[PDB]
Image (cartoon, rainbow over all chains, first blue to last red; front, side, top):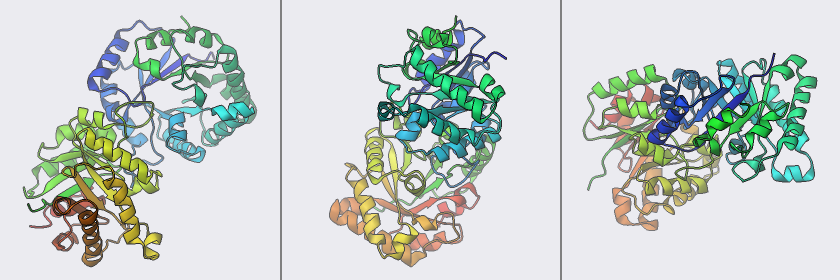
Length: 247
Length: 247
């Protein structure tokens, strides 16, 4: 029953073979609680390298992929490829995809469906913009986004939901345990009414947005927060402390 | 003086380590004219592998990249990383990038400025849609696109221009020698007046769009056609014949 604590580190567009080699080496030797399910999202160009060097017990995620195994889509990679170099995860719908690169709710949905069908795990990301929180429609927005994802999920066994206030990524500012809980509580209440009780109880909803070693203990303490999507801090040694938020 | 024949093979979103390893092993063995400058665009996830396996004498290109070395751009790779695995080329502004992934003239122009500054070569792509060619405005559109590129090029020595009628990609239909020449002649003419005669006389303008082993001899024979950007045929054995289009 109990939802296994889940921490993904999203390196974004960072590192080279040597810098990432050192990051991975530290992580492999770090004292980590076995309690935590760790996944590292590597730049596409280093996915094969990352999977080779990381301990088999730490997962590897592509930071994005497309919705078909092959085709005339210059610049894109597919789940078939991600599988081919031994990774088992993809991050889809990240805020930067949606808002920097105009990836639509409808497209993220198609991508989720294909990724799951090909046997990847999906970290599906949702989140409201600052103007959206200003007008008071956070719930309305993340429900919308979650629905586009959920329409395309037959089986939640290999999905993790990452809630990430867009306005909290990379800025100095995270939500605070209570604010976070209010939205994670809502997303789970949504999976309750729109999917099933068993899915709401077993599906991990994780918070991202300026997570640090200094603020994670308190966030993880919240009942409906099952872990983190970690941006900046995933490049640093304190990623270890965030993996251990609960211990 | 004479502009060296350039043939790039854009594998698009295709292959795995085994299929791409076989394609590569054939190409390394094939009887190819030294005459020709060959570059293969591999999926980002296989760039390192591709460069390792391909003979040094054949170039490798990323099929896309972003416009800063590092940063919060989930899913992107930079010239820095492309360099870091030993590749020296990037394809920018591919039809699929502009019209499937919405990439603007201004962004492409930014990417070109950055890739060149970081010491990659660029295959910069331009091309008109079927509906734009119907309205008689092929000239206007490829000029528009080339200006966005040329505004951002201080040095043309490592740029190659690829003209690729969008509607001709992946369909059964290429332009025919005459229709292609009309455009290449015109694009050179634009470089002549907008940049210089020495840039116009030294810069390679290559054609893409359903180039096969069966039609390439005739296309390459045209005076202002300096090579090919090759899609589907690049996966096949007949890529060799296209590299050999002049002999």
